[PDB]
Image 1 (tube, rainbow over the protein chains, first blue to last red):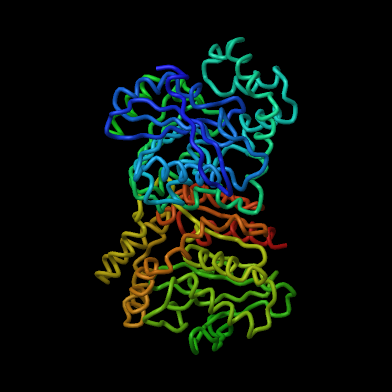
Image 2: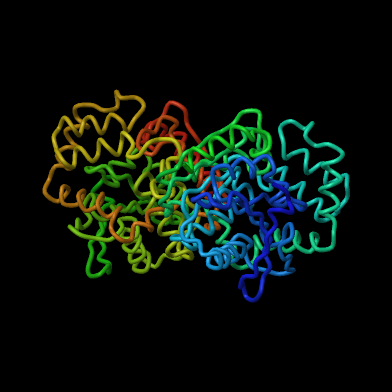
Length: 282
Length: 282
């Protein structure tokens, strides 16, 4: 399975044509699962989920979607609350590929989109696996913006290799994962004209006029499906205290916390994460 | 100051005439403060706040109101979400006595009413002091119903002296405060026909069709005034973990927790509570 063998494009309607790029694998497996990646500026499906897509594809029909503003999907300069916007695009995709009720796996920003989708189109979303998810989290103890959020804002204001390395280093517990090669690769994607355009748009929309759409902790008590929250104990972007309202209010919630693991659960604990996901989704 | 020297009655409109009983003190002091008592079946203003009304009256114009369904206020057999109902009655009272923006002090059920009033009639409510408040609390760790809530439900189903003593004993840290005399006095009030009528109505309405009005933790982020949350560390009705969403989301929130103190903060820590209240309200 390669980036190229799996690449797919689709055009959907969200206030007009919108191009979405995704990776498809495991065709011929009966149950479809959608993967929604994290929100780093140079993040994409294929980088986010490399230690995962090939494994989940042994069991599932995997659709790993590049969210609007990331990877090879359209990067608009303007949009409403991001999660609601990305949700609208996913709905368009679901309709065009002929999907009914599908389970969603989403980390960080992608988790917020999974949830917003599950709330906005209740019938279209099955079981959810959410890793250090945004949106449904509210940091009861950590002052906001957290260190991770602050370091993303700083890179947006001053897009240097130095500031990007600093951001990447608070994504993981084992800082040795932040190699010169990873820094350079992410930087080349994150500092392009398109990416700078996108990033801006995103942070700002969390405070437009539809800001309530982002405060999903006020709504998750409406969710009727099983939801597996997964957290790294040392998550410095969306810290563990953010899990509490959602664990309490989602009727069929479960929580798994891994010690010695940061914000990139799917990377630092890829084996454990893959197994936990395969079981949860059947 | 006596129960009799302070007694007052007012008729207000809430889907029709509704009688409210209250105690007035400190007339001639410039700043008015409203006190809203707790929700035990035989609870009332004058019993709830005896170690407090006379003290606060040295500084303030005190209006301690018996909430609908308690004390000598009307006890209707039917009403919507309780806090929203009691809020409507307070609004009627405010309008008739010519009050503008007044600070509110409320414990337990009365705290939920203060908050619901502050949200429903944003201009009418000044600073809030809330002791082990219901409504704005959500117990992130304690399974619901808590022990205190369970023991109230049991008395409602089986109104015996034995079951009432058991309920009273989880209201305080120092169980020695639960004397034979206090048990008997509360029982004589709690087991009357009117009180049984009222209690029923209350628990049930938390689950009518307007149940969302009771989930105030989803709304307190709209509150613009200073709010002093006060908790007993050993509160077994609305436990300390219930304070967290409100402390985080209310911009001008403060929290004070007293060790060695249960659900009746105004009783077990009456000196500390009175001083903290006088300072906070000026």
